Image 1 (cartoon, each protein chain N blue to C red):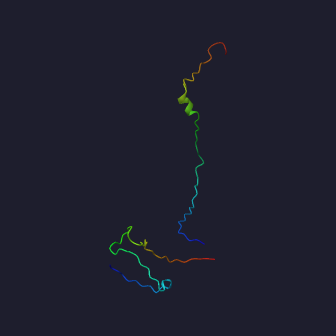
Image 2: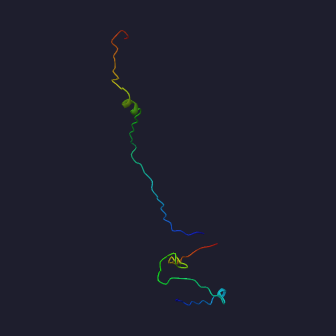
Image 3: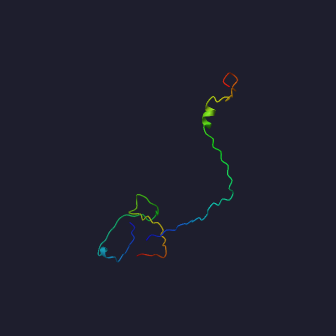
Length: 52
Length: 51
């Protein structure tokens, strides 16, 4: 069995362990990965505005 | 309080007229004459006792 260790200092995981099955060979959506993060690249806009 | 790019077009023109001469013709019942048996409006000319 093969494992990958992850860490976050975030608080709600204080002494909390979660574990599940993931696949490290596919980058594409498939019914066999725990979750997929659909990401749209994002850009900013800068302009001058009047408000009240 | 919302911003959006706009294209403004404000024309300024006026039609000036000089010549005080104009000729107009009005035609009516163009439909009917083609549609109807419009024939010679012959002028029977008053040769019998009426004159």
